[PDB]
Amino acid sequence: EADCGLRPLFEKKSLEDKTERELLESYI
Amino acid sequence: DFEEIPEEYLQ
Amino acid sequence: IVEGSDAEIGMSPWQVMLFRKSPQELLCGASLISDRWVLTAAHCLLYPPWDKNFTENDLLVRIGKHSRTRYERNIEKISMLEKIYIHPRYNWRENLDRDIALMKLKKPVAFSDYIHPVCLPDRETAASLLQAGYKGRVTGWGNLKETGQPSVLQVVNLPIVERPVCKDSTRIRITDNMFCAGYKPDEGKRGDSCEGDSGGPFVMKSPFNNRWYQMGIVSWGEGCDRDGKYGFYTHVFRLKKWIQKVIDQF
Ligand SMILES: N[C@H](Cc1ccccc1)C(=O)N1CCC[C@H]1C(=O)NCc1cccc(Cl)c1
Ligand code: NA
Ligand code: NA
């Protein structure tokens, strides 16, 4: 789908879940 | 251990 | 999930529960990849060593859930299966090579705050993100310990492991259709998939376009959260040609 992977309650509202930053910090 | 689901889905 | 935590509401809106009609029980995890297609592990449906051979009418999928056992009225959606497709070279005899299956729903599911599909990786996203040390995320309702069960969906973040370390951790033959993930004994942190998490998604959030991609499927492990052992996940991108063939033709 065209909006796959964009969560209604997070990405679509520009809200961050409590641990996604841990993933980003690992992408080095 | 699971709450019974609606009969509709078991038809 | 071992050493994870409770999911937030709507954190994994592609999460699917595979549910047995009779007796009514959880069978596996799975993921929503479109309004009519669900992805899971083949061993969730077919595994002759355990006399497992499920057909469509044996099964339901439950989408939008949080609680493991409650019927989440006005939130979850329960769908019947039209057809199961198992990879033709799924190796249930030896090492679960190509542990992947698709299920088509009898009717398309309506998306909502709690129900939304995950992306499948393109070649470039897979090459960029499937690297040792980079972390993904596993979700499921499986056991909390190897030797109990959670009230709500569990989440754990785990690093991808160098392929020589994966190979040196087990006597089972690894293939390019697998990768492994988890912390090393010296790294301190813990966590793993376990029984009942089978078929659920290993996802990563692309830093290039801020979308979630499903890189793996919960496939196999020796024990759960054992020191020096790692969980093994089906390599979704490696098997995407078969995925596309099934969807294009069915
Ligand atoms: N313990 C076996 C090991 C095995 C691997 C390959 C082939 C035969 C046996 C296993 O994981 N099995 C036996 C068949 C199903 C699968 C399982 O329990 N998967 C769930 C699981 C548990 C812990 C970690 C993960 Cl990633 C997945
Ligand atoms: Na080995
Ligand atoms: Na381990």
Image (cartoon, helix red, strand yellow):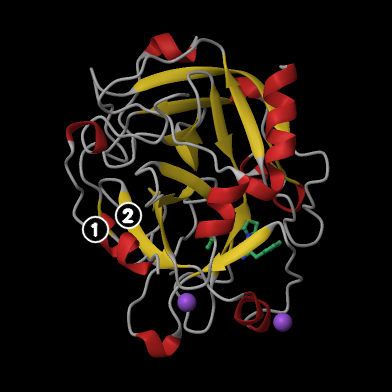
Q: Is residue C213 above or below residue C1?
A: above
Q: Is residue C160 above or below residue C211?
A: below
What distance separates the C-alpha of mark 2 from that of mark 1?
A: 10 Å
Where residue C65 appears, x then y in whole percent? 31, 33
Chain bearing tag 2 is C
Give the class, few, some or many, for how many residues have Cα within 10 Å of label 1's Cα (few <14, many ≥20). Answer: few
Where residue C32 appears, x then y in whole percent? 47, 31
Q: How many marks?
A: 2
Q: Can the viewer see residue C217 in this picture? A: no
Q: Can the viewer see residue C70 in this picture? A: yes
- Which one is nearer the viewer's eye here, C33 or B6? C33
Name the amino acid, label 1. Thr
| Location of residue C109 by image quarter | top left
- Which one is nearer the viewer's eye here, C33 or C151? C33
Which residue: 38% across, 59% down?
Answer: C1
Left or right: where C218 falls relative to A22: right
Name the amino acid, label 2. Val
- Which one is nearer the viewer's eye here, C171 or C205? C205
Which residue: 21% across, 49% down?
Answer: A17
Where residue C56 appears, x then y in whole percent? 64, 23
SS for callout 1? loop
> Which of the image's four quarters has the C terminus of chain C?
top right
Determine which residue is flagged by label 2. Answer: C155
Contact flag, marks 2 and 1 (Cβ < 8 Å): yes
Determine which residue is flagged by label 1. Answer: A19
Left or right: where C122 falls relative to C52: left
Where residue A26 appears, x then y in whole percent? 36, 68
Chain bearing tag 1 is A
Q: Is mark 1 within 8 Å of ligand 3?
A: no
Image quarter where ligand 1 lies: bottom right
SS for callout 2? strand
